[PDB]
Amino acid sequence: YQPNYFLSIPITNKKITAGIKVLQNSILRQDNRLTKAMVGDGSFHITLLVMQLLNEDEVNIGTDALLELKPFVEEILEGKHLTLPFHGIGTFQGQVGFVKLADGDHVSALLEIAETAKRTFQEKGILAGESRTFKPHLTFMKLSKAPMLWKKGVRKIEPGLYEQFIDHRFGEEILYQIDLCSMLKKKQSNGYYHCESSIVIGE
Image (cartoon, rainbow, N blue to C red):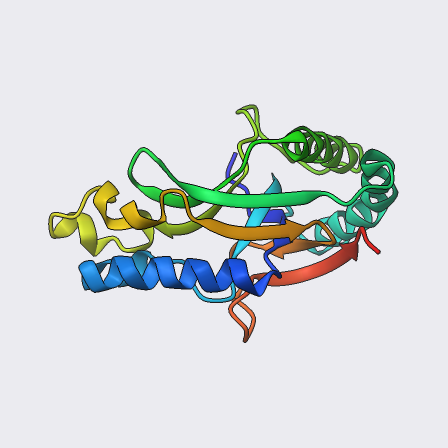
């Protein structure tokens, strides 16, 4: 199915987003027509769960399900913060560029949170989650965002473009806020997705 909503972990560590800005700019000085492929300032996030919310009631139901999820995430973390280290760069078939989530104990915990999120939402009547493997990543560019690129010979992200950032430590994000975000609504003033509601997992 086509999702229109998602649970989002926003990137709040300014060092991470500043490092990505540098990466994006270095790519652009090499090839400036990649401008519209870059994800917008202020939009950086990890997608935790996708879903469909198709009316006002369902948007309210999503918000309820997010609230209900909070204690579950607290249970899962067992008194330790979840730290997500962002290191290196990867692509999905040369069309989507992303900062990689480093391997570690956090990946399994994150996956557990994603599956518990999927269950919590479905038990409230929300079509959520996917059948494909959860592979969290921090997107910085998508060629699909700039349709004219095909139309003029740019049909893959040149791996040389981000060569210098291949083993760049962008930084670490501690899980705290989880946002319920609209994919299709107008973005916030600061560049972030439209947010229906948020919880904090935190403190």
